[PDB]
Length: 99
Length: 99
Ligand SMILES: CC[C@H](C)CN(C[C@@H](O)[C@H](Cc1ccccc1)NC(=O)O[C@H]1CO[C@H]2OCC[C@H]21)S(=O)(=O)c1ccc(N)cc1
Image (cartoon, rainbow over all chains, first blue to last red; front, side):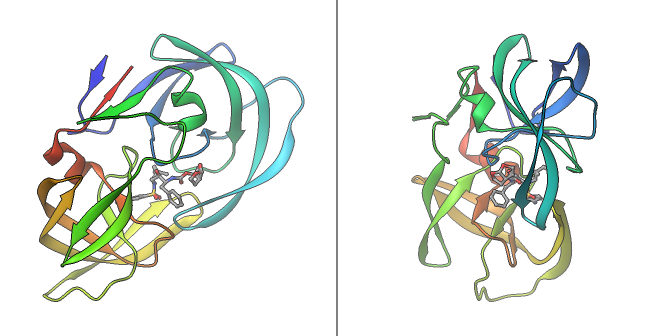
């Protein structure tokens, strides 16, 4: 679909058999989700945003469906202010900026 | 034009008679630019993201040209690690997300 930016581009995602709302974030290299339980192994990592760095758990090769489009990639889980879908997954669903 | 998200969507902007590289960021509510000496009055503000909040100066009705598309609106200035074009100006240049 075509999404205008008058409001936050929030969309429903499905990860680990659970529905959630997430922000399509072209300014994020990576996908960061709020605290949740995900199966499989994970590795501790650090990510930095506008206000500093936070500790996150990195989950690789995770299936996640964004607005009816499937993707399999890395998902970081930690104390982010909001679920954000970053470019690592936006590319998988064929998302582009157009003006 | 169309911009893919394989790499950061950086573009050239023109503000206060200066050319800069800025990020087209659908996840950013409002434009925030790296520290620069803009004239005129301003109002303090704090914006939050990954890692916490930063203090910025809010300038109103600032003219910015993004990829030859003129815009005018709020521009925040503060210790951001990167110039960010937010939704408040992306709408003005007709920018949409598409997949
Ligand atoms: C609350 C939603 C989202 C986190 C908000 N951010 C925009 C976001 O695009 C930032 C914009 C951003 C990009 C680069 C450095 C600092 C901020 N990206 C980001 O934090 O991504 C992180 C996750 O992937 C990694 O790639 C980029 C940093 C990591 S932000 O920078 O903090 C921001 C908040 C309010 C305004 N008005 C303008 C910008």
